[PDB]
Length: 158
Image 1: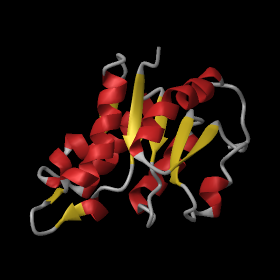
Image 2: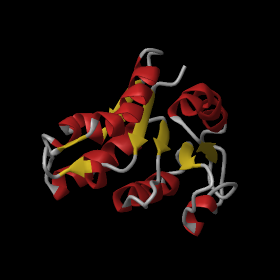
Image 3: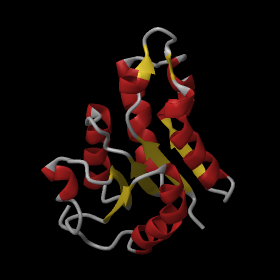
Image 4: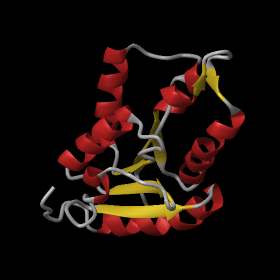
């Protein structure tokens, strides 16, 4: 039973400047994943919900500290690197892989991602989950999380 997960992905890039929040459509995948884990007893750390989807942003300094500390606390790191790339999420991918965390990276099917992201497969404790929709993520995530977590602490190149 997975104790806790950190869920990362594009955020500021998805906030509508006119309303100051993410659209319901853009929130959907995050809320679905949050509920998915929490209903199974897994605590979820996630900036989007923490900062009310854009309405209660923290400062650069406070966001940085919290994201880093919650990634360090969480048993598993799950994140969308983003199309286009989320720069903040890529920093977090660095933090998590540098900590030797079990990681599931959620990559859009047929989209291009960076070499230092796809190259982490078999260099770190990482599973890539390519997806074409939210239901597919929900159906496959538990198996992926379980596989990486099963190898937690085992030595990697990183």
